[PDB]
């Protein structure tokens, strides 16, 4: 009640807590990649839609928000659909949006972000080619 | 048997119970968010299916139950699949369902619920944009 | 606190961990197929575009990179579009690219790769007909 | 759990089927499926904690 009720359990406690190793830490960091890589095709593929109706892409200062809402800064868009070509803007969860480039150096458009490092254009400058 | 059997254990009891601090309380509340955020894409994405066959979304009074069962209140749906586009209706565990809006103010459709606060349209009005 | 706090839980632990069987392993391997099969039409269909402007296909050593960038190795291409007929080159995730053949034995062109086996021209020689 | 011996036969049945092992309900029962389900394509049932078939603890799917 004092010893058997305790001593037997002290062992069972450590014996239990000792051989219970669930998993690692950092698997979410790997997930951050595909979350952004998923955006890549989704970004360019979505921009291509706007590149079809208005026959071109939005400006840097015009930002991806133009894909979210009608491009107030000129040039204006024709047959801009409801809410643009996206429901909402994917916010990079490190305090940054997906900064597009007008014109892109790897093609028609380039996109960039701080990324997990939280630094602009250092190592986690992903968003397109580089 | 009376002192060693006890006094030694009284210490072991408190020494054990003192330095055993497992965790916090409230982690489940954080989980309630993703549980609802998971619905968000699942809700709109599922509604989009109905927006394809019948080329439109169900009415407010028609509710999300139309996604569960054939929409009895008109307009009627074409090629409505078996059991609609969902197995069962996700019940918000605070006494509320996911009230859709016909038409949505943030787009084609808007969804709302009481939420953890259990209040209608106060702070936990999540279900879509707002 | 020592027995009820433990013994009841030891059961709940095993009772829980025992009847929680989520899924299999190897489903991704099945996905590797369609990922490559998706390339097949995308490869030949994309090459056909180059077969239109320059009225022919790129050379083996010229590789699919010619579809990525202007074909430096002659013959030269006419009206080669921006960045060629593709954004980027699909890299087979087993240390190999999609080796084209100039001329193909199953037609105008043939493509090959190591594949999941990681072996050249053994079993996972997919990329076109064979 | 294993390839369906009773016909109809399955195509591209993966290794060991779609599960490691069968979850045994710890009250002397397995998860009895229904062919075809009344709440949809398939329905599942079990004795449950009551240990009674189709009384109160008939969970396994919709009902
Ligand atoms: Ca950076
Ligand atoms: Ca509220
Ligand atoms: Ca091979
Ligand atoms: Ca029963």
Image: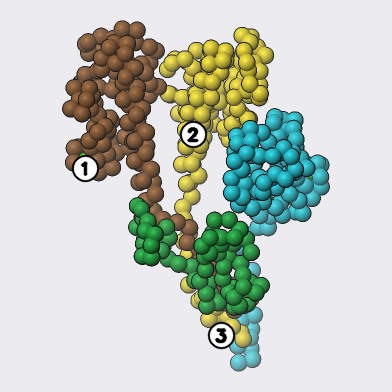
Chain colours: A yellow, B cyan, C brown, D green
| Label 1 element class | loop
Look at the numbered disc 1 and say if its residue's Cβ is closer than 8 Å to ligand 3: yes
Question: What count of labels does the image hold?
Answer: 3
Q: Which sits in the foreground, B76 or A23?
A: B76
Q: Is residue C43 above or below residue C10?
A: above
Say which label, 2 or 3, has the lower sequence index: 3
Q: Distance between the Cα atoms at labels 2 and 1?
A: 31 Å
Please name the residue shown 34% across and 24% down the image: C45
| Label 2 element class | helix
Dot 2 falls on which chain? A
Determine whether, in the image, residue A104 is placed left or right of residue C120. Answer: right
Dot 1 falls on which chain? C
Q: Is residue B46 above or below residue C72?
A: below
Where residue D39 appears, x then y in whole percent? 61, 58
Where residue D58 appears, x then y in whole percent? 61, 70
Dot 3 falls on which chain? A
Determine whether, in the image, residue C96 is placed left or right of residue B124. Answer: left
Please name the residue shown 25% across and 22% down the image: C63
Residue position marked by numbered label 2 in the rendering: A38
Asked whether disc 1 touches disc 3, contact meaning CB atoms under 8 Å apart, the reply is: no
Ligand 4 image-quadrant field = bottom right
Circle 3 Cα neighbour tier, 10 Å, few/some/many (<14 / 14–19 / ≥20): few
Please name the residue shown 61% across and 81% down the image: B9
Q: Which sits in the foreground, B51 or A104?
A: B51
Determine whether, in the image, residue B51 is placed left or right of residue D2. Answer: right
Circle 2 Cα neighbour tier, 10 Å, few/some/many (<14 / 14–19 / ≥20): few
Residue position marked by numbered label 3 in the rendering: A4
Residue position marked by numbered label 1 in the rendering: C123
Where residue C8 appears, x then y in whole percent? 59, 75
Q: Is residue A46 above or below residue B100?
A: above
Q: Which sits in the foreground, D3 or A7?
A: D3
């Amino acid at each position: 009640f004092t010893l058997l009720e305790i001593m037997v359990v002290i062992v069972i406690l450590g014996v239990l807590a000792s051989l219970v190793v669930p998993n690692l830490m950092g698997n979410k960091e790997k997930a951050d990649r595909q979350k952004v890589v998923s955006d890549l095709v989704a970004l360019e593929g979505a921009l291509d839609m706007y590149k079809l109706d208005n026959s071109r892409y939005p400006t840097t200062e015009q930002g991806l928000q133009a894909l979210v809402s009608a491009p107030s800064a000129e040039p204006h868009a024709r047959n801009y659909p409801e809410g643009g070509y996206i429901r909402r803007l994917p916010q990079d969860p490190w305090g940054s949006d997906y900064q597009l480039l007008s014109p892109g150096q790897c093609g028609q458009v380039d996109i960039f972000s701080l990324g997990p490092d939280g630094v602009p254009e250092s190592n986690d400058d992903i968003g397109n080619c580089t």
